[PDB]
Amino acid sequence: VDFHIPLPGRQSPDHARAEAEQLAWPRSLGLIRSDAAAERHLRGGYADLASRFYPHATGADLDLGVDLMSWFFLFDDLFDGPRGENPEDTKQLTDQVAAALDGPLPDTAPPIAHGFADIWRRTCEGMTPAWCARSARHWRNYFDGYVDEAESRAAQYLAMRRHTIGVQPTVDLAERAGRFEVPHRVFDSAVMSAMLQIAVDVNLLLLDIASLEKEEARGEQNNMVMSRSVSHMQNEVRARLEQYLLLESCLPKVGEIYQLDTAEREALERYRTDAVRTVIRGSYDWHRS
């Protein structure tokens, strides 16, 4: 599926290691129990993914992203059954996990939940408060959507799987890992927001053509396709990136506009290249077909 993402692909020089100790965390958290589930997990190349979403994270930082990614797919597995077919139900879990953004949870709490909590802890630990509060809301929306999606008892779809995809939490993570924050003043910008929306959509599209042969065979008929549709999807991605660049260029000017500091300007730059860009190129540098 030849696309048009005029952006350099990166991988964190540490992944070497990372991908090797990747099981450690989840096994201890109870997310992986049988030697089979560990294998299953390895075949997913989640550490390999995180390493592409966070080229700038080396070791202790990279590891976290590996987990977030790692946790992402495990968590999803929990809704592949009939639970993903009844909103009331999914939310029963949703809140147990999401409760971690409020404070410690009773041991009684499932592992998938204790798992998320440990990620959060380390993720939000060391960032400004205003940030965690934001980075959290985002998570909140992620969770919210899994329910709204479970409301299954064209563009209408995006709004739906716009929060479910979980792209933002990932992007957020780039900052978590990169030990830096985009000047909050700009992350709210009409431009940056526009840039982010794209990152999402692009991912939300690439994914749909890869997990197609699977979703086409089974039920789930919400996938963006349901050979021509493929085209205006390959096309849509083109224009999406094509514009991404246009936006990217207005960035410096956006700097003036928000009287951006002598060093906030550098911070934002990190965001463009290490958070928003990667999250796009990386998704692509993963698939096959």
Image (cartoon, rainbow, N blue to C red):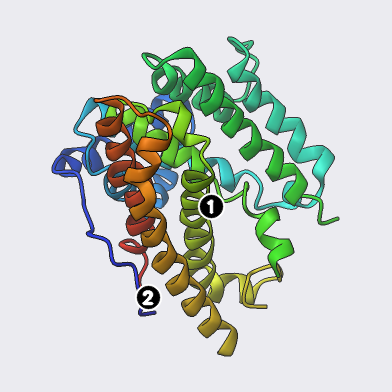
- Residue 34: % across, % down: 44, 40
The answer, for residue 67, to whether it is visible in the render is no
Q: Horizontal and vertical percent for residue 174?
A: 35, 36
Quadrant position of the C terminus in the picture: bottom left
Q: Residue at x 48, y 79 (%)?
A: 235
Q: CA distance from mark 1 to mark 2?
A: 18 Å
Amino acid type shown at disc 1: Gln
Spot the residue most to the bottom. 227
Image position of 135 with respect to 230: above or below:
above
Number of numbered discs: 2
Q: Residues within 10 Å of mark 2 (few under 14, many from 20)?
A: some
Q: Label 1: which residue?
A: 197
Q: Which of the two residues, 149 or 261, is positioned nearer the viewer here? A: 261
Which quadrant holds residue 97?
A: top right
Residues 183 and 275: in front is 183
Which label is found at residue 208?
Answer: none
Residue 87, how many percent across, how many down?
A: 81, 44
**Disc 1 element:** helix
Residue 48 appears anywhere in the view? yes
What's the residue at 40%, 15% (across, down)? 125
* Rendered residue at 81%/51% (across/down): 151
The residue singled out by tag 2 in the image is 3
Q: Quadrant of the N terminus?
A: bottom left
Height in image: 129 above or below 167?
Answer: above
SS at badge 2 = loop
| Residue type at the position of mark 2 | Phe
